[PDB]
Image (cartoon, helix red, strand yellow):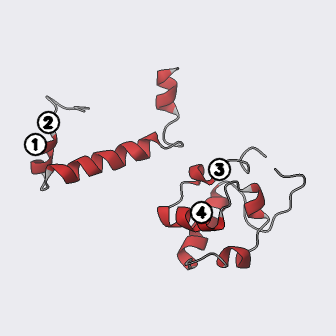
Amino acid sequence: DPILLRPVDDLELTVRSANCLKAEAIHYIGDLVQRTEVELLKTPNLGKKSLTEIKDVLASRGLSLGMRLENWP
Amino acid sequence: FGIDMNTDYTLEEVGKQFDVTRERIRQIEAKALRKLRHPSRSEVLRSFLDD
């Protein structure tokens, strides 16, 4: 899907979440949804607020974590 | 920029307007332009550009 190869820049996330994903270095969301909640809680210096916000934005576009993809990117 | 107003006002004038130095007003303007340059909120205006 085009929206999952879309860089995180356009997710409309706060700068704290930007720093968190820079630490994780997940630029596109297609491999992001494949990651589970714990795999996002392994981020350095990340808490409940960042994950609830990222999940809220994922849901704003009808997506969430733990999904499966094939031949990505 | 003078939108929906009479003669526009300088950085100093707008800063003294509510209560602030000019530098903070410049920071606020920069933040606003950073937001508007961001996509999502920048679809119709770019259409008005038609470039």
Q: Earlier in the sequence, mark 3 or mark 4?
A: 3
Q: Amino acid at mark 4?
A: Lys
Q: For the image shown, how many numbered marks are present on the structure?
A: 4
Front one among A34 and A45: A45
Q: Amino acid at mark 3?
A: Pro
Query: Label 3 vs label 4: CA separation?
Result: 12 Å
> Which label number is shown at residue B13?
1
Query: Label 2 vs label 4: CA separation?
Result: 40 Å
Query: Label 4 vs label 1: CA separation?
Result: 40 Å
Query: Label 2 vs label 3: CA separation?
Result: 38 Å
Q: Position of residue A6 (x, y in %)?
A: 68, 47
Q: Amino acid at mark 1?
A: Glu
Q: Are marks 3 and 1 on the same chain?
A: no
Location of residue A21 (image quadrant): bottom right
> Which label number is shown at residue A7?
3
Q: Nearer the viewer, mark 2 or mark 3?
A: 3
Q: Are marks 2 and 4 on the same chain?
A: no
Assign a secondary structure to mark 2.
loop
Left or right of residue B24, residue A70 in this image: right
Task: Identify the residue position indicated by label 2 in the image.
Answer: B9
Q: Amino acid at mark 2?
A: Tyr
Q: Residue at x 66, y 60 (%)?
A: A58
Q: Nearer the viewer, mark 2 or mark 4?
A: 4
Task: Identify the residue position indicated by label 4 in the image.
Answer: A22
Please say if A42 is above or below A29.
below
Q: Chain of mark 2?
A: B
Please say if B17 is above or below A14.
above
| Cβ–Cβ under 8 Å for marks 3 and 4 | no
